[PDB]
Amino acid sequence: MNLYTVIFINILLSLTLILVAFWLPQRLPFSMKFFLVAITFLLFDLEIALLLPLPWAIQTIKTSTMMIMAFILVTILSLGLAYEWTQKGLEW
Amino acid sequence: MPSTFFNLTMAFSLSLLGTLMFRSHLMSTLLCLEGMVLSLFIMTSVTSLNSNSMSSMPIPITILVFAACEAAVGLALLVKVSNTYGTDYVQNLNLLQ
Amino acid sequence: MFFINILTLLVPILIAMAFLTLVERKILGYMQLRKGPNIVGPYGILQPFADAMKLFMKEPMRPLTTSMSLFIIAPTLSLTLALSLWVPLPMPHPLINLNLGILFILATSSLSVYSILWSGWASNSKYSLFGALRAVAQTISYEVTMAIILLSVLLMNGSYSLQTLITTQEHMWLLLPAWPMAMMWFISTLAETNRAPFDLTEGESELVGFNVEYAAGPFALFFMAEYTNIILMNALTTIIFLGPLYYINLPELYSTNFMMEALLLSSTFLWIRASYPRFRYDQLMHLLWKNFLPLTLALCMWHISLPIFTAGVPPYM
Amino acid sequence: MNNYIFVLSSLFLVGCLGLALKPSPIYGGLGLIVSGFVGCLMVLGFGGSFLGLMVFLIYLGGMLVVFGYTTAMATEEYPETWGSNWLILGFLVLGVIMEVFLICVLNYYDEVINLDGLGDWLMYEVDDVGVMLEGGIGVAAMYSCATWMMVVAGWSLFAGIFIIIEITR
Amino acid sequence: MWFEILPGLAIMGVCLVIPGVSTAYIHKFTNGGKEKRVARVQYQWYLMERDRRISGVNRYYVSKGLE
Amino acid sequence: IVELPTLEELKVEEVKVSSAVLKAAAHHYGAQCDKTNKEFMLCRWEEKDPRRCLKEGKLVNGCALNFFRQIKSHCAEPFTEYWTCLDYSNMQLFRHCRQQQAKFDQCVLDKL
Amino acid sequence: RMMRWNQERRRLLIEDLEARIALMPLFQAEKDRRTLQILRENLEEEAIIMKDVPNWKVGESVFHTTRWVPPLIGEMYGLRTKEEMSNANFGFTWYT
Amino acid sequence: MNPITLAIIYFTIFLGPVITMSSTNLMLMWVGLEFSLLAIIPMLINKKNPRSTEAATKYFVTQATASMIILLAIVLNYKQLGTWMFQQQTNGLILNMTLMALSMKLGLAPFHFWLPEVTQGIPLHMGLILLTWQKIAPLSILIQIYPLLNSTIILMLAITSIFMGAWGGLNQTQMRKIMAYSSIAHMGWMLAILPYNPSLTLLNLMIYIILTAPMFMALMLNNSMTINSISLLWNKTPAMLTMISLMLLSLGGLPPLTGFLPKWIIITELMKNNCLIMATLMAMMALLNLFFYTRLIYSTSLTMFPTNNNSKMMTHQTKTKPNLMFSTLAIMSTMTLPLAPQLI
Amino acid sequence: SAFLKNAWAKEPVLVVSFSVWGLAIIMPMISPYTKYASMINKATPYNYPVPVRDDGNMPDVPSHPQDPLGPSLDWLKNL
Amino acid sequence: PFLDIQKKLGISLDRHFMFLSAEQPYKNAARCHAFEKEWIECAHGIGGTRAKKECKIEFDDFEECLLRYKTMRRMHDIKKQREKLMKEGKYTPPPHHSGREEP
């Protein structure tokens, strides 16, 4: 609720401005590169997700498995990047 | 959840009715397709959360990770189509008749 | 009382927004051998209020070919997200402390990329669409390293709550450790606020894209948003990496030093702008995907290893 | 307040109604973003922060930004068809109202809605005196307890790059 | 001379300390001179709530050994 | 039916002191009163039904109550200073207050 | 320094978790005591309203097992103060 | 394809069905299905011809929505039983969803429209994988859950498929689509006996795989996607004319060849279970399938279609040989019938 | 080696990048503290430690927390 | 399942977390853990066909711990009467609803 209170004031402040602002005064751009980036972005964005729980997982009793897992994830994605570089990708 | 899991379920059916009746742009389907994954993600997370079943929270996310790539593939097909036909319009996709 | 506090956070920040503009127009000036604006008011203090009034009075123009919502939603979203992200910030006490605070800041920032996308589609002129597509790309790319750099931090903080870092940085700034990422957080903070070295979102010599069709009130709202962000991101640098001294007995020396460090790092991106030419569109992405992302991903692993083998796993909570 | 979750759930349904009526691709995207936020708040209402906020990070700004992105280069301009966007708007509004009465009808069938029992069920049980019972502790089983869940996903992403590049080529 | 840039910075600064001092005294006023309890985890909310029930309705009021 | 115990059956004295107070003395309560505490707890776990272990629970409050009465008798002032400083902190963190803690802990090693 | 500081912090993390560990038994006795009271109190009102009900015992476990069952927060407060209900449902999330 | 990519994809197309089969946590069964969907799409557009993009975009949408429906069934179960897997108690509608969905991925009956079209725009090779190593996965999920599914629906999808497959095939002249149609039909028999004796589904599949894999490597030996194209087989490579004849009649149920056993034991099992209504109608239109099989026989073997002079040129050059698999899978298929008892 | 050298001077990020990748893949293996992480975190007591009945057949379990029996974290102390 | 490469290899990558009574992190027991156990140690060695009739007491209960619908019903029923009774002025919430507060 406290957040809700703050946020609605936040929208209100902005809608107030635009309203006064409008009331006081009284086709084929495409490059696979761009699409490709967006894609890569999510592949990385998803990975960010699988990496986000790492702060809670640090405290996991295993530890060895934690790091073994996390290191494998970071390494396999980075190799994905590596092949992106090797291929024309990331070379715009 | 008794009736809060019926809204989400009908959301998935309203999204179901969407993906199944195409109209012009293909993107609207894909986009719709995603509306389901959100509804599934929300429902899976909701019940896992009120069953206190923490062993299952992995799933709500595995669902999203697989769904994201699934969509990545879907959009690359879409880009491939408006590279071959200049539009995403489905009617164009009628050569295999 | 809560509202009083709501007012105390938003109103002052907005006023600070305004004067940043003035300060940007004097520090850039003296660096370029010119006084800057001093004639309106005393020493230019009334200068920010003056053009605000000129901007709102001038006729908002709705291009013949323009959506009328993806056009008015875009500045509202930009101001709303930027002012909103000041809600959960430790100074030292946060208005609304959130257990997953840094994820709130990362998520809210991410949403601003739309405003750029929506404004570019809404304008319906070529300069706008080309600018938006490159812009969204810049912002998004600088999100992938931006997020990983934070994940490295968190793992040495123990939690996502920005309030924990005040207890993590009671003996030393997180710059000493993790300086290599500070730099990479600072450069990413420069990209995400489309400031100079990375101002291709709206290059002026290149596509005079974001506000091409935006004048008067819409121009102002993003405008305000950018500058508030300019501060917020600098402030996040001043909590996450430069930890202001915290004394539980007197909470304001935390805010006094937060004031000093934020102003200096806010001064730094002003100083960066005048000092450097703007990077090329691909030169910008070449940096993040080639130069920074491999550094960040590897240093990310070093920050999952530093805790374990140095038996320093951070205390949750 | 006790309806806080019903309402949010209701708005979600509408949001999805929008996507279904297939408005212009980019406006539809706006729709998925609105539903997205509503949904996030739903998960953030049943006690799950990580799961929710992740929805935001990966899906609100993360995934659909892409959708909007691609819906910027390849889905044309939805030109000469924009007019329906108004008709669709109407049916949406009409449908919303329809449902309004609709659920009232379902409420009538006591034989779920628990009209009186609203706000009594968003949560069911809690470890009142517990400490480490926060959504996320679970999401981390992915690194240790459950890793299969990670090795499978990881492969997906990895293979994903090779796949997308191959389809795109 | 550069000192003229200071007037503007000062106004910015004063307007960036207000918020931090304000939020951190409108808390120590509403919560009875004691920092607002941060309930990160339920236990804390429980203890907090328990406090409410213990006295008045507000948790900040705190009963002691003399009760 | 449900055989829910009656109120008179469950009306026992309790500490009823601010969380901080318990916290301030917690370390010593975990010490002077676990013999009975544990018992109540062991009753609680193995016999999932609380209703079955209610008695042990009344013993719990009681043991603690005197624990407090003894504190009240000796080194009370110290304890009063320690809790007041401990309560001011938002997470009632133990390290902000160590000088006050040393007094009371020292005293209870002289008097109790 | 980071290694030493977090090791200090971890020790502190241990020092206060154990502090509740010690305080928990009391809370358990308290919680249960109060929990039952809420169930029973609801029984009183239950009988008062279910007596007129035709051949409807005042209260009966929907589950035939005789094991002790924790009540849903909804059961405990559903017929209690709505505000109380709300506090239990979304109170912590909104915190304080 | 950078051979590395070829490996990653092929591994996924192969890890896809294998995870499905091995796991019991349905979720892990769903992602096995998901990986198969992602891996197959790149190969489908290898020529990248305009027909291909159409194929993949249809295959993907049909596959994706079905995948989402299968996930919904798992999500619903999770709330009707905490388990992540179907159980005796499962709500009937929950299982029926899984049948429809899985019958879409496998392409049975009223959802049989995507398969013929994707089989038409993909290469002969990827045609085989799309027909036979992508049916193993979904069928595994069904075979595991057989005790619980509905006998009525399966039968309706079974009978429908048999009819649609047969009728569709009669008109088609493109080979890829004749096979697509046959697969719909055989897939039908398989799903008919699932509720009663799953073990026979696994026979009516293997035999279909041991029949179709030789048949397609035959179609591509001369890469003929037309019957007219396969009819000039007599000039391009005369020996395969004999076995192509028997394998196609084997695909239909004629008695001396191996192909009779799957139909015979499925009919024996259905009569044992008393469906002498259903079994009879299926066997009868099954006979329609042989008519279009024999019409092809006529064109390719029993009658010699006229050829082109330029063919003499292709004879001169040594014909790249058919892999050994053709033989071992042609014989084990055309004539194992004398060894039926041990097969079942 | 020679390229290594130029690599150190040209494209000197990747070099550093990889170096770190490795150093993080080694230090854990070889360190006098790695073992502590799984212990220090194991020890941190989050969930109540439920006491076992005294059959009286156990000399290992301490009958009282402060007893000289049981586990100790003096390793954590003076760490 | 169809191909049990897991039991054979002895690995358990997919079985440890299939039911609510499986090991939950930090041993935070799930809800309905009091029943699912009772409903799966019952149906162990007895196949499904006979885990569906005689072990119906434990599922009928576990179908109520989780769904918790009979409770919802009883409760909803209670309220209704209370509403009607409150109409006649018969029921007046006791101050117990607002009494002292037990620690």
Image: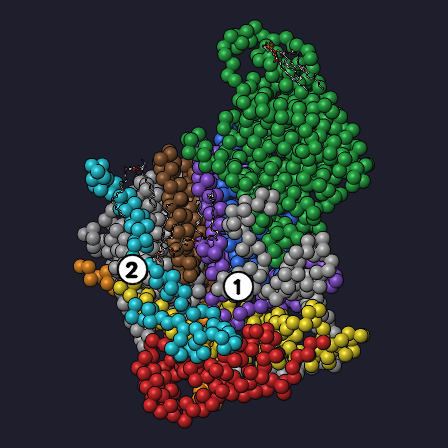
Chain colours: A brown, B blue, D purple, E orange, F red, G yellow, H green, I cyan
Q: Secondary structure at mark 2?
A: loop
Q: Marks 1 and 2, Cα distance to the nearest angstrom?
A: 40 Å
Q: Secondary structure at mark 1?
A: loop
Three-letter code for the amino acid on which mark 2 is drawn: Pro
Mark 1 highlights which residue? D47
What residue is shown at x 43% (from left), y 84% (from top)?
A: F32
Mark 2 highlights which residue? I32
> Seen in the image, is F91 located left or right of residue C44?
right
Q: Quadrant of residue B95?
A: top right
Q: Is residue F86 visible?
A: yes
* Position of J56 relative to B22 (above/below): below
Q: Quadrant of residue H173?
A: top right
Percent x, y for residue C34?
Answer: 20, 53
- Give the quadrant of the N terminus of chain H: top left
What residue is shown at x 33% (from left), y 45% (from top)?
A: C294
* Position of D81 relative to B6 (above/below): above
